[PDB]
Amino acid sequence: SLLPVPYTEAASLSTGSTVTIKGRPLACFLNEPYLQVDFHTEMKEESDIVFHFQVCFGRRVVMNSREYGAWKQQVESKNMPFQDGQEFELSISVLPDKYQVMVNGQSSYTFDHRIKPEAVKMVQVARDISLTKFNVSYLKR
Image (cartoon, rainbow, N blue to C red; front, top):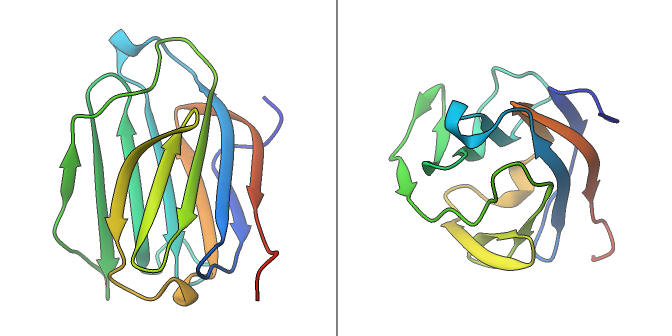
């Protein structure tokens, strides 16, 4: 739709920051579209990933970090608040100890910090969605 996917934006995060995403899957859930949001330590896409969030719509969610080139311990969830064929609003809040992921206003996933959020320099949104809104909040010290 409005914003090109894969979408890449330089970013800084600390406690109280929020990344908000509005979009829509490009396929019905039977065809298993994916959505990926990655918080990178550098602008280059091969850089380390502080927080990797990957949805297989209708099936499962996986979260992980990539540290010095190597994926760490995968966290898997079968929580699936996304709705087949619907636009979604996704919010990722930086809390003191974890990321909190809200889907359409409802807390749906969390992920404890493995690397300080201050290491993030870039956010990338990719895979099988159209993206109409992307915002990183920058209001707090």
